[PDB]
């Protein structure tokens, strides 16, 4: 097999058509699965099959039929192959169990198919301002390293049909949709122009889970503090312990939520809702202090000279009305 | 040993019977142990022995007896060997201590046995909707990379007897059972058809542990709030602190359970039970508020004009009846 | 040095005495240190020196004295060496700083000493039913990969004296003792019989630490709830808050203990003790509810017609007696 | 391509101009992205493109035009290349997917361009005394390993214009600014002098996030304890539970904050503020004890012989005044 | 450069002076930085420069001046080099970015300088009985692997001046001091005697941080329980809730401290102080139970027949005196 191909009779350190027009190379991609996603480091891991198509007359061999030959990764070190690399990637490797996952198929006229299986991790900027209602977009980029557009031309072989996805791809806490491909030209100041390929998709969260865990407990505790407005003001040993204990219960809820969320160090949409509810509970404690002080002053004044309080009556209306107004404004901005 | 075999006289870059019928290859598998399982990344790790059987007349050597020769991993780089790989795997490697774990045995007539020891990690989709009563199924897949069904034929050498398991295989938090093997054909649009092999097993949890840790504390606290229905309504400084403190105790239990469970971001069966019990505790606090307000109004009305309350009597019956009805419906759906 | 030994004149791909009796190989082991132990994955890491002894007449060289030659790891790739591997191991590697840790010493008559330094991680099944009083046993296994008992014979060179241990070996949370060696034969259905070597040791915990952290706080809280049996029954605002707060304190202790212990998902000995104490605290709360209800009924009955309660007197005796009986049964079973 | 260049006719183990003046080498750097930063281990990870420029007459080839040739990483092992390394680095590696990310361009007159893509992790000393208002500075260093200033001269090719940064570089919890380059000479006692290059940048935090999470809850609880100064002193069952519960609430806040912050084991600016507020809450509990004791003594004295207390009046003024004074001093020192 | 040195004319598999006296080798060490320290696994990571000095007449080359030649890591595989390795090390590696960090300098008369940059992790036994006042000592060991003292002699080239340290070496939570070097002979039963080198240093903690976080909160809570001794005994709804809540507050502090400290599973100095304070709080709760019971009995006895209690008076003196005595004994033992 190494004698039909003129391996030793040709210099394979130079691209086909050296000194002439650029050689076109086609790319096909099949996505196998998505492994994991990190919200702190802002990256994702993908596994895929990568295929290349090009023609090289130096690899032609005589044959009485159209039967193509198949080779392994050992022949790759001798023949010339493209050097595509993934831009903005953090780490990547090629599987080698039980051997290198590389195949080569050579047509009698010199057409070559080159395929390999590779896992790549790529960075992706994310914005958590609208958490947990945020929507994230990611992209993967493929580009030639050493050859500019004047020497190598890169394109999708079959347009938008060149991308295939496994039917079983899924994520534990995200929903994946809208796979499509695009192309663009990249420029480097000290090297020149390059062709670049893109693979795009979108991610979404499960809204209903976060509503039950975070928004639901907060609302109940706020409504629970409104009970004290209906208890008799003369029961000092009852009104005071109820108010302070509700603040303690709210504090533990906020602390627990922060520990479960990722260590994102800036204000998010969920943080605004929780701390506003904390202020409402705090204001209810000061409300009884005014009632107690005024009642004591009035009783002492009558003794020196010798029914529901007005504050309680209005608090029963103002407090529920203010909280509903806050919800309408909050949900109108954050959809 | 390298001269009895015609290593230099044959081209080993081509499969035996090139240009003719497909060469059949048999596979035997022995499972050694299961290392770990991840519920967040949805993958498992397995260690096993992999063996191949095929015939190659080019490796025949003259011998006066049936004594077969044994070689090492150094000879593998010269002779032709199958290229089986594990589909949907994330990472894998071959052990090399103190040397490569590869053996070769060649019969005088050219029959070859090839064995190696390899550890492989494979993905597995899991559903946690019925946690902690869920049951999970996993599979491992073996397939040829470069050779289609027209060139290489893959099958189990001895049918269902080709799979062996160690007697000491176990998991810390799962029960393993139902090992069996199956086969199926896989199709690739741009390459063709391939034979694929499967190894299947099932996993189960320990039910009684989760009942004690999660379901048991929740039931006791709900029954504890029903005590307030039997205390005298005139003891305002006693009824109110009891109600609010029970809500605080329930909140800490729910927070602790979430931290221990894996970060699965959707509603599970256990979450439904815990939050329904929280509502029952919340409703008991509002029940006393109605009793206290009505009692105060009645006393003031009598003074202006100049025994167990009905709500308490019915609450002693309705609340226990409602909770039992919930349990019957809940346990009938989730088995 | 490469010319006194007939490296190029002999075929080193075959074991000495090919076609004849099995070649005996001796093994010496010196344990350097134990690195770590994992209770969730059930494995341990060990570092050791491994030495081999065998005779090969093909490596003899003429010498006027008994001065043996010393070589490095480069000569290993040429001469034949044993292929011992560690069974049931998860991962292992050979150190290479600043170079490969391999030595070779060849006697004039052909005796060869082969030594290397290797770190190996091996699995070990553990049972935590009797935690924290459990005792664990571990073993390490060494076996030849490719050569059966008919071709290679493996044995300890000096019996039980072949195992040496460093004087400074220790673990942070375990006690190591009882190092000894044993041998056994292993059988493989498709390959044959093999000789196997074993290294055994035992591990124990520090009992007194767990008693102070877990058992000590639980006992104090149970005894603390018995105080309410001596307080006047007329102090309703005192008896009720004391009972409910003790339940809250007990709940936080149980939650904290679970977080510190490893994620072992089945019932252990410690879990039984903690939850039984929780029931004792729960029963004390219901005890006062019966006293309060009966007192209220009696007072109302006397009014309609126109001293320590018996329950409190017996509770002072029954509750302390029941808890002591539980301790005697619990400690008699779990030693 | 390997015959136009006199690879076999020259000794490439010696630098160009051996025995003569030092060869000047230029460096260009383009920063791609920052991956992560660790506050416990005090290091950061950076990915960048590194380029070298030098002239070597031994690589000249005849050509009728100015068309330069392009090669791959295979030619690097034959020709002489600079040996730049990153000082104070912990770990680094060169990407190799799908092949080595190395390019070579050779001009007809012998000018050589050498480029590679590398990820490097470097240490950086940090001071957390002024947390969370601290500002950190980092640097990256490049130096030749084996060749001193007498043999190799290292400099920026285009001065301060040699550094380029990606437009999308960002960090999750830090702000990056002030990229600039500097140079300095380094001296080694046993080897000599070396040229060193520097890349500098500055990092800042998000101030407003930490104020809401830490400073905001602490202030509210302190103001909440001042309420007890306005409640009637005769309500013993109300004043005492309010005071002790506030201490409990403050303790949980401090514990939660420590768990979220990195394990920095020395006093920081934030720790001072939290513990001073704890003392203010503690002092309020002792204040009521003095009032209660004095009131009891006065009442007993009057009985034996047969209005707001002064302490409460002053506490309403002294306590708010003292806390405001603390804030002015605290914020004047820590800006 | 490969022809002035007689690489092919000499057998470099044997040490210089084979069959004669031992060859002396000198070592110089410069410490660059300390990366991290682990208190659970008991190991530390260090990065350093290692240099060797020896003479080999086989590498002499003719020269008209004293100009020494410089080489790279490629020549190392041909010439003979020492095989120093780090004893008791867990893992180590040599940096290779952008190339191997190895240099060679050969004098005309055959003197050779060999330098390399390596990162090594070594074990270190630690004792935490006196935490957080403990002091730890660490050591690093260098030894020849294959050559005994009869063939290779190892020594510091310049005595105690051979060790250099970077001015910027620091740790986040430890203080490093007292760098010095020592030497000792090591014996192996089956191999012989070896020379060993040592590098020693000492580590200390920041005392004041742990006092504020652990000792300070514990003392305040104990003093807080002494307040109840000054409140009127007739206020049953005040004395009882104060006592039980203090126990709850103390329990949360102890749980939080354990989570922050490393998982060291034996009794430490800090644990003794915390649990003794817990007993003091527990005893105060039982003290009021005796007062309440005796008061009730006396009142009932007077009714049947028809002022500060003594226990409270003594408790005001005995309790403060006992705690001060404990501190004097505790701090006298643990310095
Ligand atoms: C489509 C095509 O190129 N077919 C070729 C044909 O020219 C040749 O004669 C035959 C061999 O049998 O098959 C092949
Ligand atoms: C079963 C089989 O093929 N046996 C062969 C036999 O033909 C041969 O004569 C003998 C050598 O002694 O053993 C072998
Ligand atoms: C114990 C043994 O085999 N010793 C041999 C001896 O025969 C030989 O004559 C001498 C060389 O001087 O030493 C060696
Ligand atoms: C700027 C420069 O050096 N240009 C050279 C020129 O001398 C030569 O004649 C031409 C080839 O066509 O291009 C190239
Ligand atoms: C100190 C020493 O050995 N120096 C030698 C000297 O003998 C020689 O003549 C000169 C070459 O110019 O320098 C070198
Ligand atoms: C591929 O299909 C997607 C579908 O959204 C479309 O947006 C995109 O433009 C298509 N690409 C090409 C190259 O036609
Ligand atoms: C192997 O045995 C299992 C037992 O469950 C059976 O389901 C399966 O069909 C068998 N496979 C073959 C190939 O007979
Ligand atoms: C080695 O000594 C141990 C000591 O416990 C003993 O049990 C074991 O049998 C001995 N082994 C041999 C091979 O004598
Ligand atoms: C590069 O620009 C920065 C801008 O801050 C300046 O400080 C620095 O000195 C400049 N360097 C040189 C070499 O001019
Ligand atoms: C090196 O100096 C240290 C300083 O503490 C001293 O203890 C040690 O003995 C010295 N070593 C030698 C070899 O002189
Ligand atoms: C008390 C909770 C009130 C919630 C009001 C929600 C209004 C949503 C409008 C879009
Ligand atoms: C108060 C707990 C009642 C539990 C009822 C369980 C019924 C199970 C029916 C299958
Ligand atoms: C209240 C604690 C009683 C403990 C009794 C222990 C008995 C141990 C018998 C072996
Ligand atoms: C009660 C909070 C008072 C805060 C005062 C802040 C003063 C800032 C001066 C720079
Ligand atoms: C209430 C705290 C008393 C502390 C006494 C410390 C004495 C230290 C003597 C060395
Ligand atoms: C499944 C319960 C959702 C509750 C949402 C409450 C939003 C205010
Ligand atoms: C802390 C509450 C003070 C209330 C004062 C009311 C004066 C009208
Ligand atoms: C927040 C409630 C204020 C009510 C004021 C009533 C004045 C008469
Ligand atoms: C081992 C106790 C199990 C309790 C189950 C309770 C289910 C309602
Ligand atoms: C918050 C409880 C209000 C109860 C009102 C009862 C009216 C019948
Ligand atoms: C949830 C209990 C309701 C009881 C209503 C009784 C009306 C007389
Ligand atoms: C929940 C406690 C009820 C007590 C009833 C007692 C009847 C004898
Ligand atoms: C658990 C204590 C029961 C006491 C019953 C006394 C009946 C007179
Ligand atoms: C966004 C609220 C900031 C509050 C700062 C308080 C500083 C005393
Ligand atoms: C613990 C508080 C004691 C208060 C004593 C007051 C003496 C003037
Ligand atoms: C901290 C308040 C002290 C007030 C003292 C008043 C003395 C008359
Ligand atoms: C649990 C406290 C009992 C107190 C009894 C006192 C007898 C003198
Ligand atoms: C721990 C205080 C004991 C006081 C005893 C007093 C006896 C008269
Ligand atoms: N094709 C990417 C690239 C990097 C570089 O330095 N020149 O080109
Ligand atoms: N046999 C698997 C496979 C991948 C590919 O691209 N062609 O075949
Ligand atoms: N010696 C172990 C082994 C594995 C195998 O397949 N045959 O032998
Ligand atoms: N150029 C760095 C270095 C290290 C050394 O030992 N000599 O030089
Ligand atoms: N120099 C260390 C060593 C190990 C061994 O087995 N012989 O020597
Ligand atoms: C926050 C309510 C205060 C009311 C004072 C009249
Ligand atoms: C939730 C019970 C309310 C009863 C009102 C009559
Ligand atoms: C659990 C004790 C109940 C007693 C009822 C008489
Ligand atoms: C801390 C305030 C004490 C006041 C005593 C008169
Ligand atoms: C712990 C104090 C008990 C006192 C009994 C007289």
Image (spheres, coloured by chain):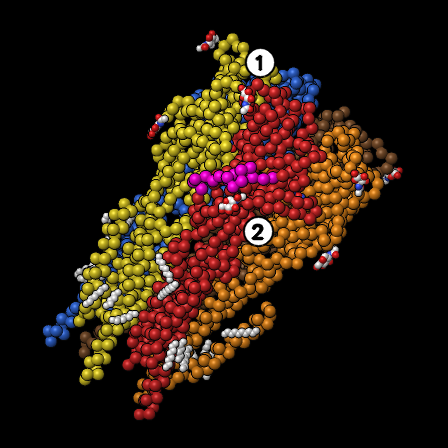
Chain colours: A yellow, B blue, C brown, D red, E orange
Say the numbered circle drawn on residue A4: 1
- Quadrant of the image containing the C terminus of chain B: top left
CA–CA distance between discs 1 and 2? 58 Å
Q: Name the chain under label 1.
A: A
Residue D168 magenta-highlighted: yes
- Quadrant of the image containing the N terminus of chain B: top right
Q: Residue at x 28, y 56 (%)?
A: A220
- Magenta range is D154-169
Q: Residues within 10 Å of mark 1 (few under 14, many from 20)?
A: few
Residue B156 seen anywhere in this rendered image of the structure: no
Tell me where residue B180 appears, x and y as whole percent: 47, 32
Tell me where residue C228 appears, x and y as whole percent: 37, 71
Please say if C19 is above or below C272: above
Q: Residues within 10 Å of mark 2 (few under 14, many from 20)?
A: some
Q: Residue at x 33, y 74 (%)?
A: D316
Of residues E201 and B297, the one nearer the viewer is: E201
Q: Residue at x 79, y 33 (%)?
A: E62
Residue D33 magenta-highlighted: no
The quarter of the rendering in which ligand 35 is drawn is: bottom left
Tell me where residue B303 appears, x and y as whole percent: 14, 74
Q: Kindly state the secondary structure of the residue where label 2 is placed.
A: strand
């Amino acid at each position: 097999s190494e004698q039909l191909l003129r391996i030793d009779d040709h210099d394979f350190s130079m691209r086909p058509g050296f000194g002439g027009p650029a050689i076109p190379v086609g790319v096909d991609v099949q996505v196998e699965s998505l492994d994991s996603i990190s919200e702190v480091d802002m990256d994702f891991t993908m596994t895929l099959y990568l295929r290349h198509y090009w023609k090289d007359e130096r690899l032609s061999f005589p044959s009485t039929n159209n039967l193509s030959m198949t080779f392994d990764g050992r022949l790759v070190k001798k023949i010339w192959v493209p050097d595509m690399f993934f831009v903005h990637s953090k780490r990547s490797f090629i599987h080698d169990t039980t051997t290198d996952n590389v195949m080569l198929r050579v047509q009698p006229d010199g057409k070559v198919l080159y395929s390999l299986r590779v896992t790549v991790t790529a960075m992706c900027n994310m914005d958590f301002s609208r958490f947990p209602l945020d929507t994230q977009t990611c992209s993967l980029e493929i580009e030639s390293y050493a050859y500019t557009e004047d020497d190598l031309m890169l394109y999708w072989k079959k347009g938008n049909d060149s991308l295939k996805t496994d039917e079983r791809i899924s994520l534990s806490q995200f929903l994946i949709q809208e796979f499509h491909t695009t192309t663009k030209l990249a420029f480097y100041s000290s090297t020149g122009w390059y062709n670049r390929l893109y693979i795009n998709f979108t991610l979404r969260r499960h809204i209903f889970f976060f509503l039950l865990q975070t928004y639901f407990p907060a609302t109940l505790m706020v409504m629970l503090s409104w009970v004290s407005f209906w208890i008799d003001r003369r029961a000092v040993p009852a009104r005071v312990p109820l108010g302070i204990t509700t603040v303690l219960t709210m504090s533990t809820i906020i602390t627990g939520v922060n520990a479960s969320m990722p260590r994102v160090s800036y204000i998010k949409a969920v943080d605004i809702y929780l701390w506003v509810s904390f202020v409402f509970v705090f204001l209810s404690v000061l409300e009884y202090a005014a009632v107690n002080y005024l009642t004591t002053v009035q009783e002492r004044k009558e003794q020196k000279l010798r029914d529901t309080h007005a504050i309680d009556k209005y608090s029963r209306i103002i407090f529920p009305a203010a909280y509903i107004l806050f919800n309408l404004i909050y949900w109108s901005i954050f959809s």
